[PDB]
Amino acid sequence: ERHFVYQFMGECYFTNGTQRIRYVTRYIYNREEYVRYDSDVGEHRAVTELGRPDAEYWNSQPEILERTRAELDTVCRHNYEGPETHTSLRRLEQPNVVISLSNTLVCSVTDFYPAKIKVRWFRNGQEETVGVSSTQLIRNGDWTFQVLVMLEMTEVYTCHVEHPSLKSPITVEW
Amino acid sequence: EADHVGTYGISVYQSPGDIGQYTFEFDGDELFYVDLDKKETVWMLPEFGQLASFDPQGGLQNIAVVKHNLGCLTKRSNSTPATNEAPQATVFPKSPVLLGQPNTLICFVDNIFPPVINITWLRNSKSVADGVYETSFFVNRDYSFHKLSYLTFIPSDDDIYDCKVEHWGLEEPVLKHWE
Amino acid sequence: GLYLEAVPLQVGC
Ligand SMILES: *[C@@H]1O[C@H](CO)[C@@H](O[C@@H]2O[C@H](CO)[C@@H](O[C@H]3O[C@H](CO)[C@@H](O)[C@H](O[C@H]4O[C@H](CO)[C@@H](O)[C@H](O)[C@@H]4O[C@H]4O[C@H](CO)[C@@H](O)[C@H](O)[C@@H]4O)[C@@H]3O)[C@H](O)[C@H]2NC(C)=O)[C@H](O)[C@H]1NC(C)=O
């Protein structure tokens, strides 16, 4: 009943697009990251003792070091500006907004992408913040998100949604 | 972290089992996985696979490397085995539940380690194979995994549902109830 | 466009 797991990953962290990239590769044995390349350091490091045989060795071999370093461009930078800009960064899926009653009004905002969104309640033309409760971002796992926003109250109530997929906000009146 | 996070290589291999998985992720979502058996790039969103490409050979090569390394690290660690975790499941609908309006029940299971699991649905206690799809294992920052199962259904006053999760970290399968 | 991936180093044991 002895089980063993290994994980390798190449992670690209992007800020203001590719103006700032951090590239990290990670070698993991049973949840123990034991060696890592990190572009902030510019070379491999043992994270634990299990990685002591590899990191310095890999650092001594110039072609290993030049190839891993360059992956910041050949993987992260390349992916972000090429495929990713035509796929993930261009995907816009407009939220569906329905209001129902639980006591409480619930504004369900479903099936949207990307995650950036603002949902606001209104009572007769005024933005309510008191007595408003939003869930965390719920990740559906299929490139969509949802958020449920409760108003403890019920007047005209309007659920107001702002999202990059929308030329102007969705307003749904109750 | 960052505005965005590309994970441009995830190779996961386990022993015994000879179980491999290779995926790409962006901002937490799965771009694709490489069907190691069929040597095919399988996109989470069909449209994407016509907007972009990935050579599945890349995935195969990656898994081969990690398979080898796992051998080496097994010995280097004195064959220390993985410690089983107890996963945690939550069930929720994709959409607000309206009777006679078709929907999708989602079972999200977190704290998956090792990445071997059974997630299957009960409809008033009978196994429901039909209209069921599952995701790959997604990586967590603590190096456990999560995985989602989906059941399409017609809501009904008369139906009870469970997500049942079987994992080595659990003695007997466990039911997560939703109504 | 083509997605390109990190390549892990292979360990000798
Ligand atoms: C999750 O979900 C699955 C599906 O219900 C659960 O059960 C496992 O299902 C596998 C696939 O259907 C079964 O494996 C078969 O194939 C393998 C090779 O690919 C083969 O080795 C195997 O069976 C025998 O050995 C295993 C142990 O390796 C026993 O568990 C199994 O009962 C078999 O027992 C018979 O064989 C003995 C040899 O050890 C022999 O001495 C006896 O005559 C005995 O009858 C199968 O052919 C897999 O077996 C099965 N696993 C179990 C534990 O039943 C799976 O368990 C779930 N896992 C969880 C909880 O995470």
Image (cartoon, coloured by chain):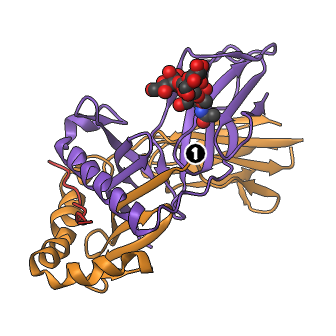
Identify which residue, B65 or A101, lies in the foreground. Answer: B65
Say what secondary structure mark 1 lies in. Answer: loop
Q: Give the residue displayed 45% in from the left and 46% down from the top.
A: A113
Q: Give the residue displayed 47% in from the left and 49% down from the top.
A: B138
Which residue bears the numbered disc 1?
A1
Among the 4 quarters of the image, the one containing residue B47: top left
Horizontally, residue A127 falls left or right of residue A2, namely right
Identify which residue, A90 or A56, lies in the foreground. Answer: A56
Mark 1 neighbour density, 10 Å: few (under 14) some (14–19) many (20 or more): few
Q: Is residue A30 visible?
A: yes
Tell me the kind of residue under disc 1.
Answer: Glu
Q: Residue B88: image x %, image y %? A: 69, 47
Q: Residue B124: image x %, image y %? A: 77, 16
The chain drawn in red is C
The chain drawn in orange is A
Q: Is residue B94 visible?
A: no
**Which image quarter is the C terminus of chain A in?**
top right
Q: Give the residue displayed 32% in from the left and 36% down from the top.
A: B43
Q: Chain of mark 1?
A: A
Mark 1 lies within 8 Å of ligand 1 (Cβ measured): no
Q: Residue A24: image x %, image y %? A: 33, 72
**Chain B shown in which color?**
purple
Q: Residue B148: image x %, image y %? A: 55, 38
Q: Give the residue displayed 29% in from the left and 68% down from the top.
A: A17
